[PDB]
Image 1: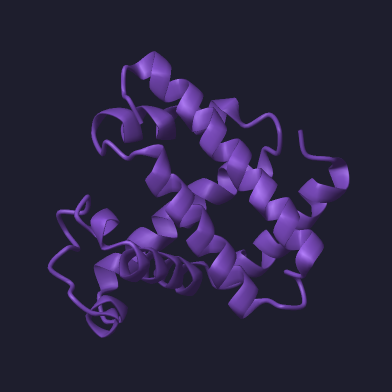
Image 2: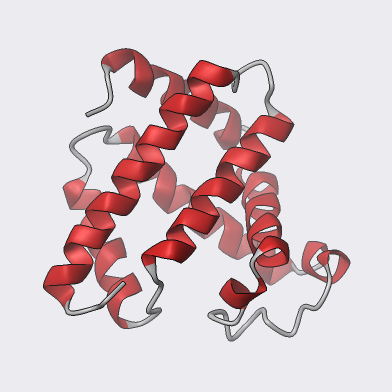
Length: 153
């Protein structure tokens, strides 16, 4: 698992995210959608957005970014004992949204990219390593639930 120090670095940079959650959520989704257009196809509401500029102007996209990062934050703050918080997310993403684990890797990388660009003082190499591990644990645990839920992931 992650060490105490690793979780501390995760929570330290997450504090920076909480200081502007909608701006971060917007930037994460835009990075995801521009880098991986196949992921955008999973969003009925948003796949009409064909450029970064149209995405930036979408208030609905911004609100969803906040929904995503709020849920992720709740999971991260549970550190290694995140199963109760993770469970409903795994269930909805295995049934309603059908999100492959690969797409969770893509959003993990988008989060890391945005944190590197926005918060270089709180997201140096050790902090990035810690967040990488935290998001790996998130994906791994979702993948385990997907199996139970009958989704190939």
